Amino acid sequence: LTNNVAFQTVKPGNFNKDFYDFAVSKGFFKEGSSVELKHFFFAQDGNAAISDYDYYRYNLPTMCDIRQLLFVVEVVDKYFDCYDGGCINANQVIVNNLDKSAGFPFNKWGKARLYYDSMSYEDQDALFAYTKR
RNA sequence: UAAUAGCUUCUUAGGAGAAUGACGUAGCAUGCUACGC
Ligand SMILES: [Zn+2]
């Protein structure tokens, strides 16, 4: 889309030296101790986002056993029989956090709050009915 | 640049409800006293 490739990196974490000093003053992080730091913020170079996406090379076209899958579907539907569902109106949709990204290209002009405010319920129902045809 | 969903903690604001207390007004019940018949 642009005239140059973007290489997004990942920063390292920020070290809470006060908590670490307090912990080691209490006898933590000793040699041979059972509790040791194993969870960190790992930094990434510019070739990270394209190296993770390349893992979609593990998705192969798999043809399933259809006489078996069509029975597994019935059993799974039996597993999902206690619930109820169906279409709701735009005034019945509850969004948890509206200060979230709206994806491309909509993140160039605002968050999801902008598009949930700018669209009335009428033209949200219109969009939903558009997606059914 | 920062997704979907769930749960939880904390803070603030608004409404509704409950409980207790306080004041004021109105209605009803009772006792005492003053006047008239
Ligand atoms: Zn439907």
Image (spheres, coloured by chain):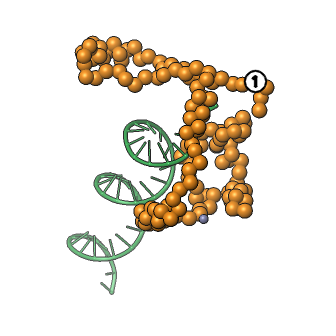
Q: Give the structural element (helix, strand or loop) at label 1.
A: loop
x and y percent of residue B14 in the render?
51, 48
Is A54 placed above or below A17 here? below
Q: Is residue A126 visible?
A: no
Q: Please tell me which residue lies in front, A15 or A91.
A: A15
Q: Which residue is mark 1?
A: A4
Amino acid type for the residue under numbered disc 1: Asn
Q: Residue at 62% across / 21% down in the picture?
A: A46
Q: Residue at x 58, y 25 (%)?
A: A48
Q: Is residue B30 above or below residue B8?
A: below
Please provide percent x and percent y for residue A34. Answer: 25, 22
Q: Nearer the viewer, residue A83 or A57?
A: A57
Q: Residues within 10 Å of mark 1 (few under 14, many from 20)?
A: few
Q: Quadrant of residue A15?
A: top left
Q: Colour of chain B?
A: green
Above or below, A25 against A93 in this view is above
- Quarter of the view holding residue A78: bottom left
